[PDB]
Image 1: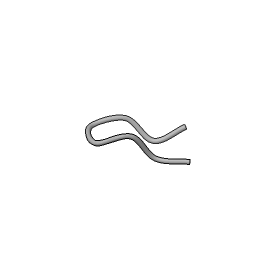
Image 2: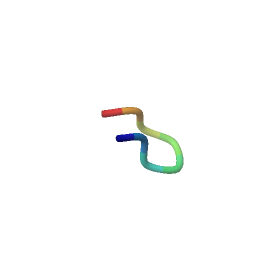
Image 3: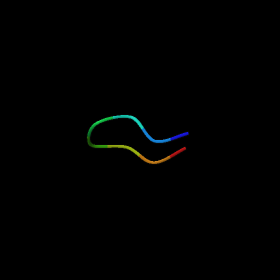
Image 4: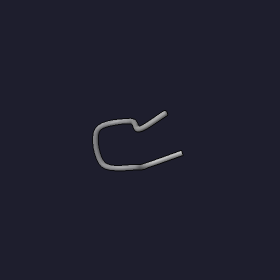
Length: 8
């Protein structure tokens, strides 16, 4: 699931 400048 995506964090603010990092998609994981």
